[PDB]
Amino acid sequence: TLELLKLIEPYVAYGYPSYSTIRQLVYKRGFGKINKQRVPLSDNAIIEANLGKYGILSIDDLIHEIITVGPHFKQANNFLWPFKLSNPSGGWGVPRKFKHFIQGGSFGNREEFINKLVKSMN
Amino acid sequence: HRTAPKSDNVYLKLLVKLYTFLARRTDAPFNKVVLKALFLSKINRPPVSVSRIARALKQEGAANKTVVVVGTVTDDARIFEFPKTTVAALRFTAGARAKIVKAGGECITLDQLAVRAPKGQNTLILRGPRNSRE
Amino acid sequence: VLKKNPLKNKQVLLRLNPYAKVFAAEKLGSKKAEKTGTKPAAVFTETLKHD
Amino acid sequence: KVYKVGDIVDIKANMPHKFYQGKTGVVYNVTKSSVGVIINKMVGNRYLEKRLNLRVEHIKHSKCRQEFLERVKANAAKRAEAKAQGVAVQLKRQPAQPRESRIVSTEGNVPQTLAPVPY
Amino acid sequence: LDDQWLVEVIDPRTLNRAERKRLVKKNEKQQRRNMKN
RNA sequence: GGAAUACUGCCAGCUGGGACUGAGGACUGCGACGUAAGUCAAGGAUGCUGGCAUAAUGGUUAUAUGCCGCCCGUCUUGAAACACGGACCAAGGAGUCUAACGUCUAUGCGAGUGUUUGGGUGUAAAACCCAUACGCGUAAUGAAAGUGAACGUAGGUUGGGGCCUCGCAAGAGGUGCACAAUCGACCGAUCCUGAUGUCUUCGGAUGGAUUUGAGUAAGAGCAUAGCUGUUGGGACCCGAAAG
RNA sequence: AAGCUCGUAUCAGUUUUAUGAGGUAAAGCGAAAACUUUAAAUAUGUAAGAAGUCCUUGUUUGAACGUGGACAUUUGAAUGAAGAGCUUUUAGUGGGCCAUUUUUGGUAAGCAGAACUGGCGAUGCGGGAUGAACCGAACGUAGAGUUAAGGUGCCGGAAUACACGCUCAUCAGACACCACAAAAGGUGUUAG
RNA sequence: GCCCUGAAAAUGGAUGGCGCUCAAGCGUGUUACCUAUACUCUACCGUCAGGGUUGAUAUGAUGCCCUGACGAGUAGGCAGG
């Protein structure tokens, strides 16, 4: 995966998400994939009747599997539908956006400030 | 993979209605296949002689299996003995029908068949030859 | 018919995660931590302060 | 060392004639005068067969399936042993996982501060 | 052609050589004619 | 020596202001608070009050103001323009019919099929009835003379939809339509093998090695109609230098 | 388009792992760059299990041409997905510019040949005062919100904002560049 | 590093205009703000896909219900009017 990220560095802004942002992202934009139908979580039995095979039978079990990368993480991570975030609600914080985060831009690895950016994009 | 019969046969639409309901509420693959066949054009619905019906009843334990021809059941003056097993089909050319009955059979149609076997138990689905004309 | 956001809507927030009630009941978002008294090492102080 | 029709080969050299020079294709005719090879050449988005004769002075035998051989042995023998004495298998290859914590102790490795002076 | 390593088109190099042999033989036939006449 | 503040982060921390929206339309679910009756911010807005009831709101329209908007169609696709047509209005105005093949679909009957050249009859160019022929199809292959498709349960093999058997299923066995891959069988042509015998050149035996055929190996066609394709007729419409 | 044969444990403009080659050269140590072991990506190449895996004998110990027999799913790397396959079929299509990258040859200077990748055409929208190719950009009808590229004296929505330096031009500059006149002059100024 | 010479004609003239000089110029930093058919959420239309339903006592089965994603378009193609 690190090779994939190196390859698409110019077009993404990745980082290391923390517990709090994982939790809010999943309670707010958390939508599950069920028969290819982007069903919102909004429940427990929803998650349960698809991810019961892996013992994930709440939403905290799901957040747990995602954050403490687990044995069934591929299953959880493909159950979740790609979060569709809003534009950042404080601006991106730079005049021009397509430079590496290191050169005062926004793309590329951002090891720990991804939490701030994402909470704002939420 | 067309999803409606292009014919405006009142009776074909009644049969398609019956078999949509049966295929929707039985879960026995016989219904799925017989329905999918009820949508087939005339060059994909080829005729099954009574000879192939005889040659199929020749098989092992296929003595009392009724045979099911979604197309039509023509005749073959090139045989001289027919078994006495029930045959269900759409259309029965009068020669073949008289032959089946003279030997003693029964040319039930597809809805008498629906009653006699909803899941399709104990039945042979025969499809005629197709790659003749090219 | 309508997706109601947790992290507000306490009713939804407690429908999911039946634990949020004890969270708030013990005030676990503001829990202290005992006073550890491990003064550090001279070598570490050196290699920090010194050039 | 002699050839047979259909073994995945390599190529090499001992100039600017026709530079494939590195491709691994299948031989199709073990002839004395030459060896013919098929190449999968992409024309737009079209993998085509390119037939080309070569002289055997610049051709070596690829061995790219020897790894699969060795690992078939490894995995079959391992799962057989695991059926013999039952523990977890994990009989699949993994990508490099990230390292975990550790204490880097300075008792003799006191740190040394350097800048582009060079010194 | 009897030198390089691959040609990208029964080896065609030998065919090159035999074609040249037919050519020079045609030369020789049209020379034997000229020296007979 | 002991502090506070800053910075960074966390709260399923408290609290206030503003904007837009209110889709759905008996009940059912997940919850929560309460002992329980019940209640609730929990599968989408209700409660209270006011003004007017008609040009007040909304629609149409002329104009004003703010911002936007290069003239249409065609042919070159690049000065992507140039160039060519356009004064204005009404009516007319350009892929049609037919023959022959072919495709896909629908309908009738089905080893058949096709009544309409013609006869009979008639409420009269209609409808209704009909004999005998004839076409196509049910037999191929040969340059031609000609010969002309079962050793077997029309064949084993490998898949194969459906069904049967077992058990709850999974899975297992059984049979396997269509079709395909492969090896065999049969008919015709080709090369040999050459008889029983012969008016002595006619007759053509067994087997094999080849090849090959839209070949057989329990038939699928015939007719009508609709949509389309190609060719030919003036052939989408107007326009040429002529004999 | 239809037919039929799967809903593929199959595929993918992708990564990894393996082994390839071009090894440029940082190795370095050789006998005194002196080798030759070798290395990162530089950029391609084939391969990673169900018919696989084997166990048992007929064959010119080898290689297998024949069997028969075991290991269905920890059944063999990461990631994504259901649109994958094959027979019959049928309409339009054939012209051509710009840029980037790899590369061969060039001279007044342009440039010419390749190969690959975008874009343009069939394509609107925001910005660059205007515009074939420049910068953003997933076009149903509307509401609210937040931003990209570009901006915030006035035209013109948005700081005559804050902070550190520099410059005065007898037609500055706001340039677009990582181009041309461009090599120099100057008792202009600033820092080295 | 800014600055000045570092050549260029001919209707009147263009940093887009006005104008600007501790800038409204040049280099740079931190903020705040403005705005696209882009991104998020909601409502409506349509198409595609996945589920459900031919049972009275009431309908339109070519229907009715629930759920999700998507929507430029020439030559051509298909469908409903």
Image: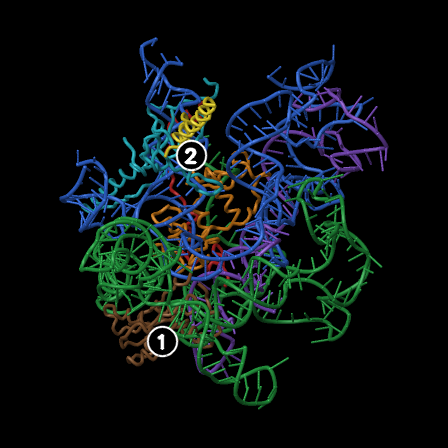
Chain colours: A orange, B brown, C red, D cyan, E yellow, F green, G blue, H purple
Q: Please, what is the three-letter code of the amino acid marked with disc 2?
A: Val
Vertical relation: G70 (above or below) A8: below
Crowding near pointer 2: few (<14 within 10 Å), some, many (20+)? few
Tags 2 and 1 in contact by the CB under 8 Å rule? no
Q: Nearer the viewer, residue A109 or F29?
A: A109
Q: Nearer the viewer, residue G69 or A99?
A: G69
Q: In the shown orientation, is residue H49 left or right of residue B106?
A: right
Crowding near pointer 1: few (<14 within 10 Å), some, many (20+)? some
Q: Nearer the viewer, residue C15 or B111?
A: B111
Q: Secondary structure at mark 2?
A: loop
Q: Dividing the picture into quarters, in which one does residue F78 lie?
A: top right
Residue A8, given in percent of the width and then of the height, sits at 48, 40
Residue C34, given in percent of the width and then of the height, sits at 38, 42
Q: Can you identify the residue that label 1 sits on?
A: B114
Locate the C terminus of chain B by quadrant. Answer: bottom left
Q: For mark 1, name the chain.
A: B
Q: For mark 2, name the chain.
A: E
Between disc 2 and disc 1, the foreground one is 2
Residue D71, given in percent of the width and then of the height, sits at 27, 39
Residue F120, given in percent of the width and then of the height, sits at 52, 88
State the mark number for residue A81: none
Locate the N terminus of chain B by quadrant. Answer: bottom left
Q: In the shown orientation, is residue A68 left or right of residue F191?
A: right
Q: Please, what is the three-letter code of the amino acid marked with disc 1?
A: Ala
Q: In the shown orientation, is residue B41 left or right of residue G69?
A: right
Q: In the shown orientation, is residue F76 left or right of residue E21?
A: right
Q: Residue at x 57, y 45 (%)?
A: A90
Q: Can you identify the residue that label 2 sits on?
A: E9
